[PDB]
């Protein structure tokens, strides 16, 4: 009913002679190699709407038919989307058939209204000790994850997906906003092996929906893919009534993509160069993540800080919404401590005694004090000496080092490649376990007894086993066996070990090859549309 | 050179031709990826491609962003 009027990059103007589509409505272009969905951005006047494309606009002709769907982008929601990968417009990109849609919901939605909001403030118990003590997660909150590569972020993502599904009974949505496709495939395959995503007949036992908008998608497709993740998580909140986790992987790339679609729509950029609507592009997304009377959405969203500048307007606008930060560090990760949550850098707004209670608060406030006093004397130890300083300053070092060990925890999703079983640690067992290390009920136990254990009922059961070990090392003996001709051959006997490698001078470079004959004549189209050589003179 | 293609859009070439050369070099290199072999594509000065694309966009009166680059 509408026809393409202008194609300027990712921005399409289409023209409706009848009634115009509403702003944010979805338009489908009739007859195109890929399904091209346009989202109406503004009404330009003279019966023209300006649209941002969710796919490539190459091959688009002025006057192509464009059908109004009468609604915004509508995506499949429900339990049938669990364990599936879905793109921004709702199509399966996991190559496993159609998505069993319980309903199809508009991805554009106002935030839950004031009466629908919950006036209460409470902890999302995660089963991770360092997260439940030192930086608790608000149910319905937004959590910044300051990880990276090799700090075990993905195994922390899958452990949050695991423990929220197991304890609180809520599902998860992973919205990968502008992610590399190599990394989005890595998360898919690691979710398959760790059990949080299942394929085939047991698809319904999955705990996570993956909603992917990759980096090679146009900036409109990446700017809306976090709202497709919202809409899947809002069905579980409002219809299923659950406590949903939502992972917006790189909320900065949400900002960055929305900043590109404002620049393509001809809007004057704001301070440092973001869109003028930066606080309402974020606040439109972040306010749908809340607690209602039905259920909750809690968002763990990864935060990139541009140019290591916290006062940049993209993190500064994001940090107004964030209720906790979990900083994953490499320094904690090379000490073998997993998860690599920095116990001092990680912050929470939920960590004040009017909302978690004073018996929880003073433990976390006391644990952080012990770790802080230990790490400001590390230019006292290396400069002067270990046995230099006082016995009380050594009492903290012994207490902090078995606190710094006790923040480690083995994960249930990591046990398929680590052997150590997973430990869900309850909240009361975390506080009461850390009261004791703070006072000194376990100063006699070794520090590596406090390592990769569940709670304080398991620190005693690790110091018992290690202490005995000296009773069971007099079982056998230990010296050299047959110095270097036991099974260590000669080097020229090892050259004849080497297997045959067939090296072809041929490349095998014409497997199934067309080899079209290309002529260097210039071929054009005449006015019939018939292909013809280029006419001779101008 | 018996394993190498060279796609060369030099300095005197038009800015559309330096914009399209990493893409046309990639399509030549995507032949080996798609037929089971292995490719190595090198876009030497990808920062010179973006300068050529900024030239086309400011001249097509597309709205500029940071350092006059497009959206």
Image: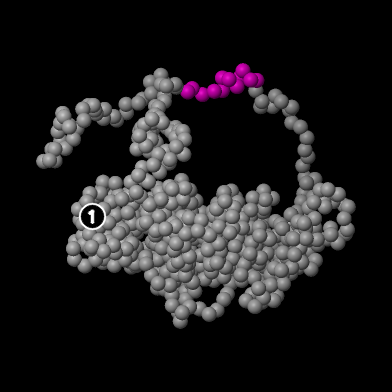
Give the chain letter at badge 1.
A
| Image point (47%, 35%), residue name | B45
- Taking the image as shown, residue A502 lies to the left or right of residue A323, namely left
- Taking the image as shown, residue A264 lies to the left or right of residue A46, namely right
Q: Nearer the viewer, residue A97 or A325?
A: A325
In what element is the residue under mark 1?
strand
Counting every numbered tag in the picture gives: 1
| Image point (57%, 76%), residue name | A121
Can you say which quadrant of the picture contains the C terminus of chain A?
top left
**Residue farthest to the left?**
A528
Disc 1 crowd rating (10 Å Cα; few below 14, some 14-19, many 20+) is many
Above-or-below relation of A116 to A278: below
Can you say which quadrant of the picture contains the N terminus of chain A?
bottom left
Is residue B9 something one can see in this rendering? yes
Q: Nearer the viewer, residue A449 or A378?
A: A378
Let me know if residue A492 is in the magenta part. Answer: yes
Residue A29, percent across and down? Answer: 24, 55
**Residue farthest to the bottom?**
A115
Let me know if residue B38 is in the magenta part. Answer: no
Is residue A415 something one can see in this rendering? no
- Write down the quadrant of residue A427 in the picture: bottom right
- Taking the image as shown, residue A66 lies to the left or right of residue A470, namely left
| Image point (43%, 51%), residue name | B65
Above-or-below relation of A36 to A435: above
Q: Which residues are magenta?
A: A490-501
- Taking the image as shown, residue A41 lies to the left or right of residue A439, namely left
Residue A328, percent across and down? Answer: 61, 55
Above-or-below relation of A245 to B13: below
The residue that mark 1 highlights is A4
| Image point (48%, 65%), residue name | A279
Residue B25, percent across and down? Answer: 38, 33
């Amino acid at each position: 009913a509408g026809y393409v009027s202008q194609v300027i990059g990712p921005v399409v103007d289409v023209r409706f002679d009848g009634e115009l589509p509403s702003i944010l409505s979805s338009l489908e272009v009739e007859g195109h190699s890929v399904r091209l969905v346009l989202e109406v951005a503004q009404h330009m006047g003279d019966n023209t709407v300006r649209c941002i494309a969710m796919d490539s606009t190459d091959g688009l002709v002025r006057g192509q038919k464009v059908v109004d769907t009468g609604s915004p982008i509508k995506v499949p929601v429900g339990r049938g989307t669990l364990g599936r990968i879905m793109n921004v417009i709702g199509e399966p990109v996991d190559e496993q058939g159609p998505i069993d849609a319980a309903d199809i919901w508009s991805i554009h939605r106002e935030a839950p209204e004031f009466t629908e909001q919950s006036t209460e403030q409470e902890i999302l118990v995660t089963g991770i000790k360092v997260v439940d003590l030192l930086a608790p997660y608000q149910r319905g909150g937004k959590i910044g994850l300051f990880g990276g590569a090799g700090v075990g972020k993905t195994v922390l993502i899958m452990e949050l997906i695991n423990n929220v599904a197991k304890a609180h009974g809520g599902f998860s949505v992973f919205a990968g906003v502008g992610e590399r496709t190599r990394e989005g495939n890595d998360l898919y395959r690691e979710m398959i092996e760790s059990g949080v995503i299942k394929l085939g007949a047991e698809r319904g036992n999955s705990k996570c929906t993956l909603v992917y908008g990759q980096m090679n998608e146009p900036p409109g497709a990446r700017a809306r893919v976090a709202l497709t993740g919202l809409t899947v998580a809002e069905y579980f909140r409002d219809i299923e009534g659950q406590d949903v986790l939502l992972f917006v992987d790189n909320i900065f790339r949400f900002t960055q993509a929305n900043s590109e679609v404002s620049a393509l729509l001809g809007r004057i950029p704001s301070a440092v160069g973001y869109q003028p609507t930066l606080a309402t592009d974020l606040g439109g997304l972040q306010e749908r993540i809340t607690t209602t009377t039905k259920g909750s959405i809690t968002s763990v969203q990864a935060v990139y800080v541009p140019a290591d500048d916290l006062t940049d307007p993209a993190p500064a606008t994001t940090f107004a919404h964030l209720d906790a930060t979990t900083v994953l560090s490499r320094s904690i990760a090379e000490l073998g401590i997993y998860p690599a949550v920095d116990p001092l850098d990680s912050t929470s707004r939920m960590l004040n005694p009017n909302v978690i209670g004073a018996e929880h608060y003073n433990v976390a406030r006391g644990v952080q004090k012990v770790l802080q006093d230990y790490k400001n004397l590390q230019d006292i130890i290396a400069i002067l000496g270990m046995d230099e300083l006082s016995e009380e300053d050594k009492l903290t070092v012994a207490r902090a080092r078995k606190i710094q060990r006790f923040l480690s925890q083995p994960f249930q999703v990591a046990e398929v490649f680590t052997g150590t079983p997973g430990k869900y640690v309850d909240l009361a067992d975390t506080i009461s376990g850390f009261q004791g290390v703070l006072t000194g009920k376990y100063d006699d136990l070794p520090e590596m007894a406090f390592y990769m254990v569940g709670d304080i009922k398991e620190v005693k059961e690790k110091a018992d086993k290690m202490a005995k070990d000296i009773a069971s090392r007099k079982e056998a003996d230990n010296k050299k066996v047959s110095e270097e001709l036991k099974d260590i051959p000669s080097l020229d006997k090892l050259v004849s070990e080497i297997k045959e490698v067939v090296i072809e001078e041929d490349d095998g470079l014409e497997e199934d090859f067309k080899a079209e004959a290309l002529s260097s004549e210039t071929v054009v189209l005449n006015e019939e549309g018939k292909s013809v050589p280029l006419p001779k003179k101008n | 050179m018996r394993y190498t293609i060279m796609v060369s859009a030099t300095a005197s070439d038009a800015a559309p031709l330096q914009f399209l050369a990493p893409y046309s070099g990639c399509a030549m290199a995507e032949y080996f990826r798609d037929t089971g072999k292995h490719g190595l594509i090198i876009y030497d000065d990808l920062s010179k491609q973006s300068v050529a694309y900024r030239q086309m966009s400011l001249l097509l009166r597309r709205p500029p962003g940071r350092e006059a680059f497009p959206g």
